[PDB]
Amino acid sequence: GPNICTTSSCQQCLAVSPMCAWCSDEALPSPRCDLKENLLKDNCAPESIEFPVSEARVLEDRPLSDKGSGDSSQVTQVSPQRIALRLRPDDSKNFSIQVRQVEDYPVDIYYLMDLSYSMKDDLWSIQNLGTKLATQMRKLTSNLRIGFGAFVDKPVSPYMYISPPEALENPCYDMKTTCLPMFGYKHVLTLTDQVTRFNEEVKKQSVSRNRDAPEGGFDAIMQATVCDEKIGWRNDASHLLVFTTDAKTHIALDGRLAGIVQPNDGQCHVGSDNHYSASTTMDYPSLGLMTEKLSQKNINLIFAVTENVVNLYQNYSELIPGTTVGVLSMDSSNVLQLIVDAYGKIRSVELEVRDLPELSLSFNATCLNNEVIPGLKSCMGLKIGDTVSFSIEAKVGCPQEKEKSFTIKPVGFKDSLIVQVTFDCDCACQAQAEPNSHRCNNGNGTFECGVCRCGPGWLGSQCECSEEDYRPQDECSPREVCSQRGECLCGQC
Amino acid sequence: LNLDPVQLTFYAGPNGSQFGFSLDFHKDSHGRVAIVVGAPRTLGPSQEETGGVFLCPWRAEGGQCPSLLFDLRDETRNVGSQTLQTFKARQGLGASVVSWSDVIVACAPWQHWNVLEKTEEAEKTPVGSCFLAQPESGRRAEYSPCRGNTLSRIYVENDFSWDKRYCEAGFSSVVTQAGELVLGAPGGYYFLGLLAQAPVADIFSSYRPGILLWHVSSQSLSFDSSNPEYFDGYWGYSVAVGEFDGDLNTTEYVVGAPTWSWTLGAVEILDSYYQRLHRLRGEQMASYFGHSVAVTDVNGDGRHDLLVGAPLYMESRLAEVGRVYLFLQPRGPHALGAPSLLLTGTQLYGRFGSAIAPLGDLDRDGYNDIAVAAPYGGPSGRGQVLVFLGQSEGLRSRPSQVLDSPFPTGSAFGFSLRGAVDIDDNGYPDLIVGAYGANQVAVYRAQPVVKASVQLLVQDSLNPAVKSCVLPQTKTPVSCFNIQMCVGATGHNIPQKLSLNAELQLDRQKPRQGRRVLLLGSQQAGTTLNLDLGGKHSPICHTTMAFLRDEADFRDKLSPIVLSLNVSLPPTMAPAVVLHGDTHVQEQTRIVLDC
Ligand SMILES: *[C@@H]1O[C@H](CO)[C@@H](O[C@@H]2O[C@H](CO)[C@@H](O[C@@H]3O[C@H](CO)[C@@H](O)[C@H](O)[C@@H]3O)[C@H](O)[C@H]2NC(C)=O)[C@H](O)[C@H]1NC(C)=O
Ligand SMILES: *[C@@H]1O[C@H](CO)[C@@H](O)[C@H](O)[C@H]1NC(C)=O
Ligand SMILES: [Ca+2]
Ligand SMILES: [Ca+2]
Ligand SMILES: [Ca+2]
Ligand SMILES: [Ca+2]
Ligand SMILES: [Ca+2]
Ligand SMILES: [Ca+2]
Ligand SMILES: [Mg+2]
């Protein structure tokens, strides 16, 4: 069997095929670069070749919690958490991970309300919500923080009524009513578990009115996500963000209508005034940036949009993984059940890859907890605290950056795994390489663990000849080792 | 393909930026061309939010361009009860610039306008405007269809219908061949979108200074629509002029609605009567299909072709990278609907398709060319222009050239791109890249293109033992063949300093010392010669002679001879030449004797 690996040095035999090895003996120059079992057959039993490790060794792992005591490390959901990988070039290794929903899990919830006139009445149904929300979420939490914030639209000329001057003070002057000066996004109440403070901070809200249907909700979502300290997201909590609105919303580059062109950056600008400081002087955020910042901070999002704009907003869920839509009632008295179902639907497992360096991975439909049922792939049915098995086949050549440790973190859960993947490509003898092998052409051959690697014309087993200089020296035969045409073909002599 | 990146024209603007939001080539009646750039956020009458337009003469070094004033003043006219007035606050003069026959049309889409009818008022709403001016003549004829006196109560009364308070006319300015000016108004009909058409001659005839109202003959405005899909359609976001119907002598307007049908997006072809002959929607929601629209016949068939930009496309890598949809003009009954080429960028958040500039025959290739821009593409999000040639049978799928932003991050290099105008008047159209908030405008000059037509003259086969040729020194009988090479330079404006270098390879597949044939003169299996074509049209054919050794000499006689001639530009500042066409001919010679 001539095989394929037989058909240059230590490195090449470690890269041509996953199975063939390079006998790294400097006492003996056979197939040489062939299968290791064949090398045993051709008497390479010591196997001086240092093969790549090509296996995963863990560095940090903890068992998955069931219900969650409350400590930072006692609510472990993902196992393993730190492994080391040393795959050979052009080699695929599949490794499995176990994830958990930890059942009981402290929750952060921020309620973003469209403070437009059209749902001012809805604000009233929100005045007494903290007690009901706490009652309906106590059964599924142990430390439930809530906060409140309002968005109307960008307070700029094409959207905000600018004359008469009383419209700036009272946008609803013409209907003989009093309202609040329009604002982009304001931080009303920080995250807390105090229902009394929540219902106290509500009832103090004065709605405003905007010229057009498309609201500025996405620009509020951006600042809610980025201002983690201001909103007060915990380092370890199930994050949510309920977002209630009735009409369309502006997207990126719409600000050209308002004349503002600077696209949404990735900074927090909600200052001490608890308002969107740079709402007017920035474009609306793109859907891609929204997905990026909703996945970087694990802040899941819930769409409580009226029946008018469900199709418009549910189609955003497709472009923003990790979000859900809900048919908010006209009176918006059903948002309690909306948040209940939001926590009961998206917290019931999403595996996503992050900061991947020449690599490729694929999960072979393992799921369940540790079993593998391809039939029950999208079966759902998970109540809470479900283990899930995910076996990803990392496929790789030899990356030049030897040191690498990439991170895998699921959607929402902060528990992440670090793979110090450091591909092994070279040989210890390759680091040695025997630059001055005495037997190789009078002590000048860089005998690379079996190959001389020298000479433009003298590049033989001892750097002495080549396929050239073929003609009818007496060694293998008095021709030109030494035979008919070029080095030596046995029998042809 | 031949756009010079190493040398660029840099034009400065105001420290308040916005210099490069929109720009165009002002074609002088005398034949000259100068670049007109709208800076829609320059200083106002008193440090106010306004616009402003600069006129840069075409140059190489660049500098601070002069400013062309159109109108910056809060007018106020008393028509009986109605004391109507204009407000320059954030008008945006320069957000849309288009030039034609000595006239420049520059728009301020967010200019405000309020009519005080005793106690009631029309509200300080952004009706927008677009000011026209002949800089040589000096005549200024400001055009603003959306300026009106209908008080807000009338709007509120029936259904808020036929509104133009916030139309923002001039969000995209174009002018037909005949001079008819076309303006977009995304906010027309209560933020729905309308269009304005009026002859620049008629605009100048009907304009009167001081008065703030007119009708200007039969100016053509778009039809108000009650269709739900058009709500917040943002029609007239981007406009262009081109011929698309079955009849000539008429100019069509292509308009883009990046938010049509709930942010889905659409593009429409209209005649002067606004009959909506064709409309093609987008494919991805919130992808902004129609942000920038271009018209040119890159296929070379004559009939104009459509390019639609969607900078907010989310590629299924769901990576937010823009995309340009291409539509060649077919000869079907209801054709043109299906896209042909879908160009997509690489850098994330690059916004590939914010500026599609027709270029015409950029490289005298016989077909028109385009330049797409991704304002935030590139290695580090600087922004990159991707030049795509005609190439016939469609468009060049790969970027024939990639122009990198020399500006820091966030400059959005490539927001406004214009071409299709030979600034060098050498059959080689140039490109201009302006960007909102860039504070600088870059200009790329095209360079002459040399196509090469290469042929070989080598004996098809021979007996290795012909033994007719004579070695000079050894005096040995050998077989030989005639080797000749002729390469000619085609194209327009080829420079006369051409120094093409031709390299020949005899038995290319065989390696060194594996070679069989061998030159008499140089004793080498391959050489380079200065087959320069500069200063003449006829090809140069200087032959060679390589001997073939006796049968007993070598053993590679079983291998057929490989004769590959490859011509490359000389390696020795700006090359100013682009080799194209055939540049490597590998005509083969086999060995035939008995078996
Ligand atoms: C949310 O996404 C869905 C899925 O794409 C949208 O529904 C689909 O919308 C497309 C338009 O992009 C419809 O295609 C068009 O249908 C009309 C007939 O109404 C036809 O004349 C056109 O040639 C084109 O084929 C498609 O039928 C429709 N399908 C379904 C099942 O709804 C939906 O509109 C999106 N919601 C929005 C935009 O608010
Ligand atoms: C355009 O060509 C001539 C010149 O204007 C004109 O007489 C003719 O009617 C036009 N052709 C059309 C409109 O098809
Ligand atoms: Ca409501
Ligand atoms: Ca609106
Ligand atoms: Ca026409
Ligand atoms: Ca065509
Ligand atoms: Ca061309
Ligand atoms: Ca030119
Ligand atoms: Mg509302």
Image: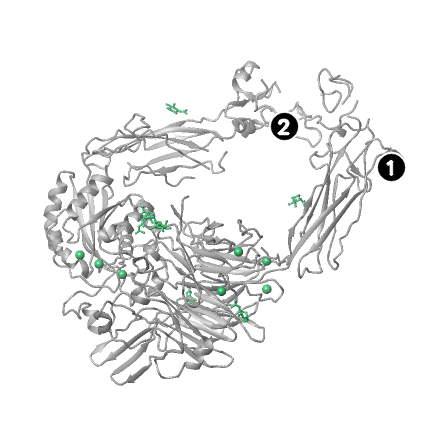
Residue B555 point in image, percent of width and height = 77, 27
**Vertical position of residue B263 compared to residue A353: above or below:** below
Q: Quadrant of residue A206?
A: bottom left
Residue B114 visible: yes
The residue singled out by tag 2 in the image is A436
Q: Are marks 1 and 2 on the same chain?
A: no
The residue drawn where x is 56% and y is 24% is A5
| Front in this rendered view, residue A268 or B405 | B405
Left or right, A486 with reference to A296: right
Left or right, B454 with reference to A276: right
Q: Quadrant of residue B43?
A: bottom left
Residue A274 visible: no
Category of crowding for the residue at label 1, using alpha-carbon neighbours closer than 10 angstroms: few (below 14), some (14–19), many (at least 20): few
Quarter of the C terminus of chain B within the rendering: top right
The residue singled out by tag 1 in the image is B471
Residue B277 point in image, percent of width and height = 43, 60
The residue drawn where x is 40% and y is 64% is B275
Q: Number of marks in the image?
A: 2
* Residue lying furthest right: B475
Which chain does the numbered disc 1 sit on? B
Category of crowding for the residue at label 2, using alpha-carbon neighbours closer than 10 angstroms: few (below 14), some (14–19), many (at least 20): some
